[PDB]
Length: 106
Length: 106
Ligand code: HEC
Ligand code: HEC
Ligand SMILES: [Zn+2]
Ligand SMILES: [Zn+2]
Ligand SMILES: [Zn+2]
Ligand SMILES: [Zn+2]
Ligand SMILES: [Zn+2]
Image (cartoon, rainbow over all chains, first blue to last red; front, side):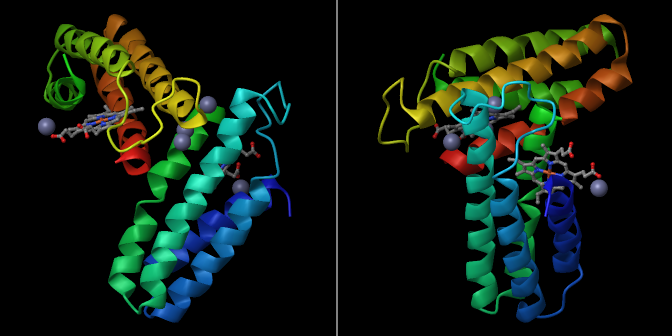
């Protein structure tokens, strides 16, 4: 999967969570988001001209996905506890993480 | 001013912008936010145990304020053009920057 595919996986599954009815649907979507975040963490932002892995902005790019994965894991803990409404609310807190990286690299 | 004061300056002036009527009110509030962001950039997050300036998470902390200042400057460009509704909307885009740093360090 490429960056576009991983982002649409994140995008579609965030919606699945919002519309979900049980913990299993939420857990399934969060698990898919988690893998897509770690896969996208291997890419580079197309508009960053310096793609060097050790550059500060590439550190920051990968770091943003570690933060996102941490928040996904927080939501998964709630989903695995059966707390559906709570997990859905935690998934909503992802969105500023998405929007922050987008503003900063797009 | 300390970190609490700078954050409440950011907090109060974001509200002033939302309720403003002309470019001058928006510009005045954004200018105050800008100075408070650069002042807060000198502090450290109270819950970060490693306060070393050269550590990655202290780099990230200061970097978040540079991003915020950049967005404030984008909003100021619109305010200085007289585009009040546009400037107010740009100020709204700050909020995920605020919430991102809060989630990550509080
Ligand atoms: C959090 C849950 C999300 C969600 C829902 C999305 N992202 Fe990202 N994203 C990043 C970059 C560099 C791009 C540009 C990619 C490119 O130019 O091809 C994107 C793009 C998107 C899209 C748009 C896809 C398109 O049709 O153009 C969407 C829908 C999307 N993302 C969803 C980088 C990042 C991150 C780096 C740290 C993080 C985190 C996210 N995105 C988070 C999310
Ligand atoms: C963007 C416009 C904002 C706004 C409106 C606020 N912040 Fe921050 N903030 C940061 C840290 C580390 C703290 C904890 C401070 C502490 O423990 O004393 C805060 C706290 C706040 C508050 C709460 C004040 C209180 O009564 O406890 C408020 C209202 C607030 N902030 C507003 C760190 C950062 C950032 C670092 C990169 C950025 C950016 C912001 N905050 C952005 C904003
Ligand atoms: Zn797409
Ligand atoms: Zn960066
Ligand atoms: Zn960051
Ligand atoms: Zn306060
Ligand atoms: Zn960090």
